[PDB]
Length: 199
Length: 345
Ligand SMILES: *[C@@H]1O[C@H](CO)[C@@H](O)[C@H](O)[C@H]1NC(C)=O
Ligand SMILES: *[C@@H]1O[C@H](CO)[C@@H](O)[C@H](O)[C@H]1NC(C)=O
Image (cartoon, rainbow over all chains, first blue to last red; front, side, top):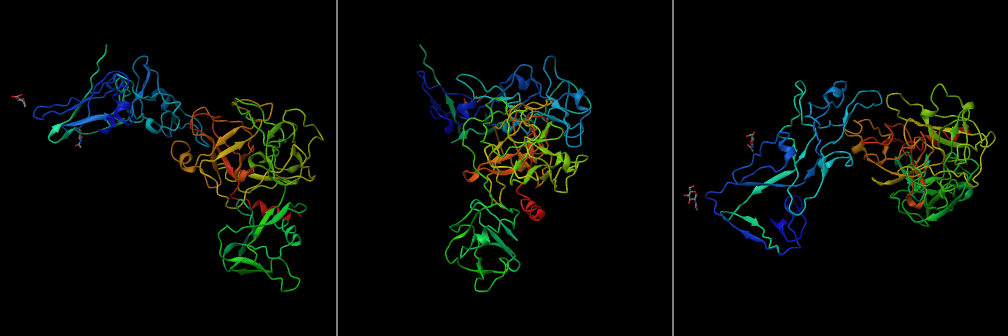
């Protein structure tokens, strides 16, 4: 709750909703009786519901906020290349076939001291803490004034299978970068609400 | 059993009862003990200096002199004492290693300005049949270090190992313009699978000069306490991009130290890096500096003085994602060389 001080750092003002500190806004903090309150918890990004984001499992009254908000391009595809990956032996990842136009993930079979076809792709281990930040397509961006969080981060190594390389989907454990808590305090689900008095 | 140590060069002394290295207090030491002490660790006809310094090393069992007895050796006259009688201990310099002309903008690994001459005064170049192949770094006028996998089979005899120093460019090292061969020691445990011990000393017959372009680099001391993300300065004429030949001029920009647990983890190098292998570079994308020389050294600058820490070794694809360079670990065996430099004379 203390993220919301007017002009601050933190999680909510940086990767959920950036409270603009220039206009003639006026902030309201109110309450609501929890007889009939159904928190909608929907994901706002296109390219996570395109790769099989169904929902969160939280409780009846838990609100899913965000930690980091990574942005990808339009041709993104978080599965490896299956027509390359078969000759890999070491560190061989899962893969599938991308949808049309979505360029593949860059995976190498480069050479060890003795082993010749050992797999090494990008985005390791997870894009939260990648070792080479200048090469994973999921670029970490800070959210702006009046924008949504453009997508949860995908761990690039739980997106795929081995036998049936279908259209490239992912798996529910692989979306990372969100947590929650319960809104209910004093038997009343608290709520923030902004106002903007323009013109 | 005697060795240098740390930044201020204290002689440690091993005793069989105490099982431990111990310092010597400066109670009536002499150059007739001191200038005759550099041949103990492989320095015959050289010496620089000796002074008294304050004790901070960390032993509580000192070494004293048996001057009350008559004419015996140094190595007999050393008993223990709890206090230094003048509170000055061994300070030493076995050779004029160290300084260069502190210049500014030598950065010619890719995207920079050339290595200024005399500011890297240990950089050599080694040749067979007058092609530039491997590098190294000088510690005596008669000894020279390099990576062992240059001197591997079937080129393991000394008479085809022509050193050529001095000139930044690929041309001006001519026949006679550079002293030449002698003994090729090796750490005799190089392998094909590990490249553990990829460091081989070399020797020359004709002592060169400390004039301008040539000066011996400082070999490190036993237990000199690096920093886990220290800056490191490499040098060499190596090809800045792979499937090249050689860069024309001397290139001497900077790199960093990666630790073990990043390199030796699962994604960089899956548990390969031995204790006698040090990682270096930056674990990043295409920001690394390749300049492949296989011996073109790793020189750091602790105690405001240049010291040698790593000589180069193998790697992966030239300066790209996830793949740093892995360096030979030349503080591990700085005494093996000192028992392979003792008995050349
Ligand atoms: C909750 O819902 C019921 C029926 O949907 C409604 O009759 C009731 O008035 C609601 N609660 C409040 C406090 O209005
Ligand atoms: C959340 O939902 C999934 C599927 O309904 C279930 O496997 C998981 O156990 C649930 N979480 C908890 C804490 O029970």
